[PDB]
Image: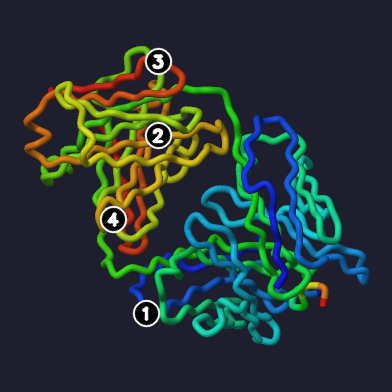
């Protein structure tokens, strides 16, 4: 769960 | 009870440095990154960048590289925005916004910080009551007001009876006739309520720190 | 970068009708990995920070009223309000949340059509706290009218004056969908005290004859 890893990547 | 509280409005001269804080409460601070969003007056939202609350590494958009800096204080659960070398295009309201747990949205937003860039100095306002000349005959409603003149810079918060009197309020946008702003506000209450019960105009000018309560008696 | 285009720019409806607004993206925002569309819809009411409405292009935020529906996929997206209320007056923004930079659209402004309404007009002489200070401001409130177009004239002893008058309109109201405006005529001390009758007259769409308010020196 993040939160600090936003977007599709 | 998740809340983002930003620091108060700032008035700077062109070329100076400003630092806005955004204190977070109600959640685990190092699990959600912090976005910064700029809003020039009357314009739309522009995403400026974000800061990772766990690593500290910021990522800025291309227009906001060089003069803008994101910062963290994890002990205080606070994010910071620093703007160096202020220009008149930096006059705006800046929001901090928390990345959601989905990683797909901005869940919670701060109230915004208005940064005004101008060479003019801070002047406190003069607050005057606005009472009707003739008493109410059969209209059953009375309109009252207060006028805030000669203040700089914006904003001022105008409430009635410390917020308890909130229906029937019209606070008008300020106009800059000279280098000073003038604003007016009106309240409409029943003729039974006034003048038996008190109504007070509360004005806050945080740049000059000029909280003033004024009764509208006569 | 990814460009988010919003359409229509602005639209005006009566309360209780359905509206739809479009958001189109330069690149696709669908990822098959989670089978989700990384597009977000925010709502911004006048004076407030943006409020999250819909993430993942269809999921409502918790507590949202059920009139708001998000829709669409890939590059084409839609926000729908089933029966608009007067509180739904706002600017609606979409945001790319697929890739950096996480760009916003230019927004769609939602305004309300109401029935026509005449202004409640109030005239106010200057305060003694201002009159002993040497300045004078005679104020006229024109509250809760629709539509926004209105004209005010100031009459001093029957002769019309337009110099030194400042006008200000509020935004559309979130509860009764009306507009309000304040007109302030600022003079000096002896200029105000050397004439007797002051008249604020208002012309609006509702009446062919203007609504007139006045006062004299007691």
Camera-nearest residue between C191 and C133: C191
> Circle 4 is placed at which residue position?
B151
- On whether disc 4 and disc 1 are found on a single subunit, the reply is yes
Mark 3 Cα-neighbour bin, 10 Å: few <14, some 14–19, many ≥20: few
> Circle 3 is placed at which residue position?
C208
The alpha-carbon separation of the residues under discs 1 and 2 comes to 41 Å
Q: Is residue C207 left or right of residue C197?
A: right
Residue B6, percent from left and from top: 52, 67
Going 26% across and 58% down the picture, which residue do you hit? Answer: B179
> Circle 2 is placed at which residue position?
B187
Going 61% across and 77% down the picture, which residue do you hit? Answer: B77
The alpha-carbon separation of the residues under discs 2 and 3 comes to 27 Å
- On whether disc 1 and disc 2 are found on a single subunit, the reply is yes
Mark 1 Cα-neighbour bin, 10 Å: few <14, some 14–19, many ≥20: few
- How many tags in the picture? 4
Residue B201, above or below B31? above
């Amino acid at each position: 769960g993040a939160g600090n890893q936003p977007g599709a990547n | 009870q998740i809340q983002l509280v930003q620091s108060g409005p700032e008035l700077k001269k062109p070329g100076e440095t400003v630092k806005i804080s955004c204190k977070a409460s109600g959640y685990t601070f190092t699990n959600y990154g912090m976005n910064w969003v700029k809003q020039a007056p009357g314009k739309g939202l522009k995403w400026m960048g974000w800061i990772n609350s766990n690593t500290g590494e910021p990522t800025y958009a291309e227009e906001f590289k060089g003069r803008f800096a994101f910062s963290l204080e994890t002990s205080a659960s606070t994010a910071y925005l620093q703007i160096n070398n202020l220009k008149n295009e930096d006059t705006a309201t800046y929001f901090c916004a928390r990345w959601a747990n989905c990683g797909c949205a901005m869940d919670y937003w701060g109230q915004g910080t208005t940064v005004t860039v101008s060479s003019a100095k801070t002047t406190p306002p003069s607050v005057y009551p606005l009472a009707p000349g003739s008493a109410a005959q059969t209209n059953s409603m009375v309109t009252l007001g207060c006028l805030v003149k000669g203040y700089f810079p914006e904003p001022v918060t105008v409430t009635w009876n410390s917020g308890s009197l909130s229906s029937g309020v019209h606070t008008f946008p300020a106009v800059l006739q000279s280098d000073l702003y003038t604003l007016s506000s009106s309240v409409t209450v029943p003729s039974s309520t006034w003048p038996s019960e008190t109504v007070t105009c509360n004005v806050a000018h945080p740049a000059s720190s000029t909280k003033v309560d004024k009764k509208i008696v006569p | 970068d990814i460009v988010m285009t919003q359409s229509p720019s602005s639209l005006t409806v009566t309360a209780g009708e359905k509206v739809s607004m479009s958001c189109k993206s330069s690149q696709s925002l669908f990822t098959s990995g989670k089978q989700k569309n990384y597009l977000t819809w925010y709502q911004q009411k006048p004076g407030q920070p943006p409020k999250l409405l819909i993430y993942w292009a269809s999921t409502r935020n918790s507590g949202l009223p059920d009139r708001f529906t998000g829709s669409g996929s890939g590059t084409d997206f839609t926000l729908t309000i089933s029966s608009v209320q007067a509180e739904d007056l706002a600017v609606y923004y979409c945001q790319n949340d697929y890739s950096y930079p996480f760009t916003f659209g230019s927004g769609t402004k939602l305004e309300i059509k109401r029935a026509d309404a005449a202004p409640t007009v109030s005239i106010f002489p200057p305060s003694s706290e201002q009159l002993t200070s040497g300045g004078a401001s005679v104020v006229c409130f024109l509250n809760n009218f629709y539509p926004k177009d209105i004209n005010v004239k100031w009459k001093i002893d029957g002769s019309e004056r337009q110099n030194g008058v400042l006008n200000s309109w509020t935004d559309q109201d979130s509860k009764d969908s009306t507009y309000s405006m304040s007109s302030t005529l600022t003079l000096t001390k002896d200029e105000y005290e050397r004439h007797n009758s002051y008249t604020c007259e208002a012309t609006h769409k509702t009446s062919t004859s203007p609504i007139v308010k006045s006062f004299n020196r007691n």
